Image: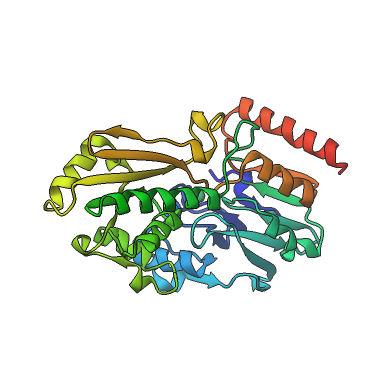
Length: 341
Ligand code: NI
């Protein structure tokens, strides 16, 4: 049965609530973004209205085979009416097509549902600034002070320079980037752009990318692995054994691999700045772990919420245990006392 944190009070709306079968009273199902924990349950068998971004809609049609009649794409940054209620979709700065949803309730309450997001100061000059937001449904993935990470830009500059050096030293080296979902596409796009190459990948991954409305995409990606010096593989294959095996598949065209494993946070964010990163190396294979996050750091999340000044916060991540809910509630109370709301 559907949780309270997936329901928008005083409407017949839900958000990211596809795994409970038919939700009693739901007239419109919103989907924030195309990551499997959020879409779980959606298939060609679904027969109620789904509201989402254009990119998400492209993925629902082509990858999950949802029938077109049930997909309702909405533009960004535009006031729209759904079942008699004013809504706005905003860029979530998460993966391609990911949105936040602003609901203007009939009784005058304003609710923001972040979906999954990486808070940014640019959000403070969006449509959110035009009126008071009363209730916040918040992506709390990294709601603890130990969770620091570098900017996306610092991580991309390190990746570009690392790849350019390695391939200029050894023109027969291949660059490999791991992936398991949409998101983090700039890692492999920026490395391929510095090397003057297209990115090569499986037919299934190419199909996905061709749904993302990336300008000039046909000049950037290919299914002809041979022709390319940057390849995509499943994240599970980014290990010494998998990378040796891949090297043997490529028909001796390369004699070395440099690989990137974009992760979330792992224990060693605590000590190490990006410039100090050194790879794990076995023979002619070297692997870099790079902390490229599409979620808010603690500091980024805190800044956003202290600017917004909500009257109530409803967490949407790590809500299955008491301990976790209690710890998050302690930080929300600190933030509120510090900022005076
Ligand atoms: Ni996500």
